[PDB]
Image (spheres, coloured by chain):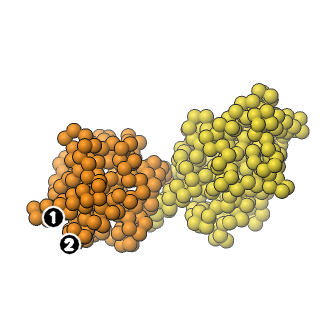
Chain colours: A orange, B yellow
Amino acid sequence: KMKKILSFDIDNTLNEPKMPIFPEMAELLATLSQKYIIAPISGQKYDQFLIQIINNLPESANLDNFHLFVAQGTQYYAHKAGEWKQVFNYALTDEQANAIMGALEKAAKELGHWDESVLLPGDEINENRESMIAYSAIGQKAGVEAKQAWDPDMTKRNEIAKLASQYAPEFEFEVAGTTTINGFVPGQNKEFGMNHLMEELNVTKEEILYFGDMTQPGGNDYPVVQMGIETITVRDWKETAAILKAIIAMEE
Amino acid sequence: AMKKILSFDIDNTLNEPKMPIFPEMAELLATLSQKYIIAPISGQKYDQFLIQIINNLPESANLDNFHLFVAQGTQYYAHKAGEWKQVFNYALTDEQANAIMGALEKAAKELGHWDESVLLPGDEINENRESMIAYSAIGQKAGVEAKQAWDPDMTKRNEIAKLASQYAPEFEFEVAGTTTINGFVPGQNKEFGMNHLMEELNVTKEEILYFGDMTQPGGNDYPVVQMGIETITVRDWKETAAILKAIIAMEEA
């Protein structure tokens, strides 16, 4: 058949925002992995791909068929013979990381959004994910209740990302998730990641079916839409789950 | 090859409540109808199946593969030789129709929910759908906006259904749709419809994929779930559309 790769953002596509996937999802992905490549592509860092997805999969999952495009596919991890390996990592220089972090910090502080008093113990706002920076306004470990209240309509993140861009015009700052702005070297977004996916997996655009929630002009899934990869827009993880349940039922 | 029947409880699966399918949905169903039977099932009456589904399909659709399980599947219409025909209709006796209607009216009136002043011209609250009764609180013709505001948490319909059941304990009252209680002979809900679907189409349970929005215990799709028929829970027609698009994509050679 034409479609070989089932690709997904994590955020609000496979899970509740930044949370472990539910058992229902874990089983669907495990079943599909017997026959298809599962290629999550997301701003999340590698350890969070493990916590959100891999650590929750049943033992029957074929982990060899989970191909992980981390930090929007600026890093890539593949599994073979019981072991994950880093295939590539377009790492930031120290200078780039500091410039990107600093721009986000200055913007957030100026706009009145930088409040470390709300942080859970040992948490931080700005995280260096090696090849990308993630500013997550009320912390990298904040709960969904708290996160969804913070910027429901994206106004805060839009204004932070705009100001960060003015402060460091040589970089790119993109709204994500519930509380996040991703900062990176320009062009190194999901378009970058998908181009790498196609090269690494030896597939054409037509052989990928992509799922995401931010597929409108300006959203972080729009680059995939615009590349000509068939994209099904979802609103939440339950929508994705219904779709995968049906795919499985119609294959049997 | 196992699934041969795609069955859908029409409202909030194929369309907005009691409304026509969107053009994208029409095209998805027409595509799937080349290969699969499309079996809509609903408390709605036959004319509404035509209005909501059939009349909106493109000419390319395979109408012979649309098998209509009307009024919960107490009626069944099939298309063959360019025509629709009624295959069965488990009509109500007059005694039954009147008892069911009267219980709903009495119950809605006692609970302060019967208001004929909000009805569109020509409209009615209780409708006799031959083999089933539908009480639709603000009329059979009300728009989605007004309907979805009337009883979004099902409070009003649950209390009306319980009191009507007290008045007429020989009948079954099921909350449905946005404004509706379906009233019928005991047991003649979607389980009855699905059994008859299996007989008429000569299929087993495993050959059906069902779609519905009320699939938790107590909801009007649970009698199908409870049979062990695989069921996809959806929330609105856009979710179903996403699913159908995916099915079609995954079938392409």
Q: Which mark is residue A170?
A: 2
Q: Quadrant of residue B120?
A: bottom right
In the image, farthest residue toward the left: A94
Q: Which residue is mark 1?
A: A99
Q: Give the CA distance from mark 2 to mark 1.
A: 9 Å
Identified at 52% across, 55% down, the residue is: B239
- Residue B101, compared with residue A248, is above or below; it is above
Between A161 and B168, the one nearer to me in the picture: A161
Pointer 2 indicates a residue of which chain?
A
Q: Earlier in the sequence, mark 2 or mark 1?
A: 1
Q: Residue at x 38, y 53 (%)?
A: A151
Q: Is residue B15 above or below residue B174?
A: below
- Kindly tell me whether residue B111 is visible in this rendering: yes
B101 and A176: which one is in front? A176
Query: Residue reaching furthest right?
Result: B94
Mark 1 Cα-neighbour bin, 10 Å: few <14, some 14–19, many ≥20 = some
Q: Position of residue B133 (x, y in %)?
A: 79, 42
Residue B137, given in percent of the width and then of the height, sits at: 75, 45
Mark 2 and mark 1 residues within 8 Å of each other at the beta carbon: yes
Front one among B242 and A126: A126
For label 2, the SS is: loop
Residue B59, image x, y percentages: 67, 71
Mark 1: amino acid:
Ala
Q: On the rendered structure, is B47 left or right of A89? A: right
Residue B31 visible? The answer is: no
**Residue A241 pos. (x, y %):** 44, 49
- Where is A73 relative to A226, above or below? above
Q: Residues within 10 Å of mark 2 (few under 14, many from 20)?
A: few
Residue type, mark 2 in image: Glu
